[PDB]
Amino acid sequence: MPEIRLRHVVSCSSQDSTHCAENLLKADTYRKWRAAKAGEKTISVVLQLEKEEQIHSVDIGNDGSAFVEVLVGSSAGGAGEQDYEVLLVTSSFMSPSESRSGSNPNRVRMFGPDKLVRAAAEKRWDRVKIVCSQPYSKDSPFGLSFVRFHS
């Protein structure tokens, strides 16, 4: 089918144990991504793609976060974690107001072709870096509710 399927969280730069970014592999079920600690200032998590393909559209939902940047890359070289190109800059869906007056605490958004670079989106990648950004917590963690890529 013309879609994208994740395999496992290749890299993790903000994931806990019980509620880890690997829960993104199970969008439905009943678990999402949660930073490894509280004080959600910025969290990063690279997910692996079950197949190297091009990216034309994406559907990721924010779980209290506000800024969401996504980079693209392949398994080439190996655990480099430094050879990805900014497919789509950080997307601002919410802000630190939701963390104050529940102003839409849980929202979601997608990234079609207009939100992805054509010089890279059309390149077959198999690894993606997901980074959320917005200082809103301190004692409790948080992150994203789900991530769904689609070619």
Image (cartoon, grey):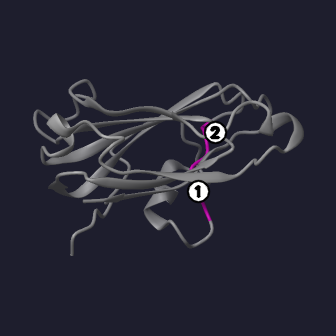
Specify the quadrant that holds the C terminus.
bottom left
Name the residue rendered at 64%, 25% in the picture: 41
Name the amino acid, label 2: Ser
Please state which of the two labelled residues, at mark 1 or mark 2, is closer to the viewer.
Answer: 2
Residue picked out by circle 2: 65
The numbered mark at residue 56 is none
User: Which kind of residue does numbered mark 1 sit on?
Assistant: Lys
Q: State left or right for residue 16 relative to residue 87.
A: right
Question: Horizontal and vertical percent for residue 19?
Answer: 61, 53
Residue 71 percent across, percent down from the top left = 32, 35
| Residue 101 position by quadrant | top right
Vertical order, 47 against 41 (above or below)? below
Q: Does the magenta stretch include residue 44?
A: no
Q: Earlier in the sequence, mark 1 or mark 2?
A: 1
Question: Residue at left 35%, top 51%?
Answer: 112
Residue 146 rendering spot, x and y as whole percentages: 52, 57
User: How far from the left and from the top, in percent, is residue 111?
Assistant: 40, 48
Say if residue 141 shows up in the picture. Answer: yes
Q: Is mark 2 on a helix, strand or loop?
A: loop
Between 116 and 17, which is closer to the camera in this rendering?
116
Q: Quadrant where the N terminus lies?
A: bottom left
CA gap between label 1 and label 2 equals 13 Å
Q: Which residue is identified by label 1?
A: 32
User: Which residue lies at the image location 70% right of the left edge and 39% below the top edge?
Assistant: 141
Q: What element carries label 1?
A: loop
Q: Is residue 13 visible?
A: no
Residue 11 as seen in the image, left or right of residue 49? right
- Which residues, given as a range, are shown in magenta? 31-36
Q: Is the magenta stretch mostly helix, strand or loop?
A: loop
